[PDB]
Amino acid sequence: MKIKQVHVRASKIKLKETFTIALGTIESADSAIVEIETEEGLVGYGEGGPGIFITGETLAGTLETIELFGQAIIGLNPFNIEKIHEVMDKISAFAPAAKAAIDIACYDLMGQKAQLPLYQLLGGYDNQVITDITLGIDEPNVMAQKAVEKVKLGFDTLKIKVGTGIEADIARVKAIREAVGFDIKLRLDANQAWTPKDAVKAIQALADYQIELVEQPVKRRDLEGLKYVTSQVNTTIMADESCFDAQDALELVKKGTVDVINIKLMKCGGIHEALKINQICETAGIECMIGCMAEETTIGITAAAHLAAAQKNITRADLDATFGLETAPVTGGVSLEAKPLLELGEAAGLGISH
Ligand SMILES: [Mg+2]
């Protein structure tokens, strides 16, 4: 198999509601969609979701980078994922969004060539995944109301955003808690909003509220501070922005900074790297959750889903980007219907088409 050509296009999908987190807001899912054509005719799909306030990447920069990658890999075999990353890495010292887009399309081609759904090439542990659904920052009573709604849809886990201040945040959780019950799992994400000691205070405050875990409580660069938190509460602390790639993961397991790690294809540059992170985490006894950027769509979510189902140590999933999309940019793959169960089929690759 040989890559004949690489095409990339912009994608802009209106979100059904304006999403808001501690780092900023977003109202449109704008990403880079790639299509890699082989000499034999097979076409693999990939996506690059740039998150300016998470990674600093932009759609303009992502599109430019993807084009440089596309011209550099013509003639290579998609199965040579090792060289493909070698090639991209020599071109750019940092562009996870661009790299993930190429990476994902290559794995899609691999699956299509082997005539196997992608999850089978990635470990084959399962052929489906269960995802939570996130609740963007808002008013305590508003979030509590939306919670009941998602639960009504069939969701058992809810990701709750916080970060305006330990005060209002605490009020937010409790409100939602005594609104849906105690059978529902509740994970919290503060996107680096708290200081070490105020983090310990806020978490302990929700001691009797039964929180599953707290995602990135402090600044991504304050590793000593993050470990401080992890080591003060018995509650499960997860690292997100503090862990982009495998080298980040190695540093965290070494220092024993957190309990769980959030993996995002758009942070590590693709499945190839995601595989590395999960392996390092599993070996260290740290489970992983597979996340997503608000800007990515069907292709990125589908790729992430196949990886999550395939790998045993990826025990949690936060693949809800397609739930807020007004329309689908492609056919097949993970539906936009808000449902916790994402079942992957027997279609080869990502199972996606124009
Ligand atoms: Mg997070």
Image (cartoon, rainbow, N blue to C red):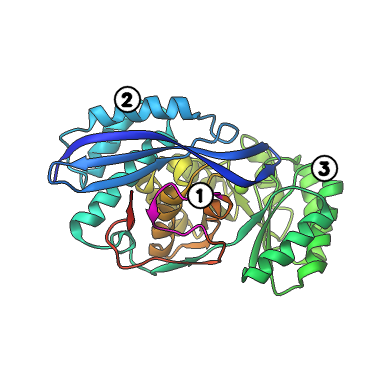
Separation of residues labelled 3 and 2 (CA atoms):
41 Å
Q: Is residue 307 magenta?
A: no
Name the front one of labels 3 and 1: 1
Residue 166 location in percent, x, y?
A: 83, 46
Disc with the residue nearer the chain's start (2 vs 1)? 2
Residue at mark 2? 91
**Residue drawn at x 30%, y 41% as measured from the top left:** 35
x, y percent for residue 324: 58, 51
Please tell me which of labels 3 and 2 falls first in the chain.
Answer: 2
| Residue placed furthest toward the bottom | 183
Question: Can residue 90 be seen in the rendering of this structure?
Answer: no
- The residue closer to the viewer here, 29 or 282, is 29
Highlighted range, magenta: 325-336
Q: Residue at x 58, y 39 (%)?
A: 28
Q: Secondary structure at mark 1?
A: loop
Q: Are marks 2 and 1 in contact (CB under 8 Å)?
A: no
Marks 3,1: beta carbons within 8 A: no
Circle 1 sits on which residue? 327
Q: Position of residue 143 (x, y in %)?
A: 77, 56
SS of the residue under disc 3: loop
Asked if residue 11 is positioned above or below residue 352 in the image, the reply reads above
Per the rendering, the mark at residue 165 is 3
Q: Residue at x 35, y 67 (%)?
A: 345
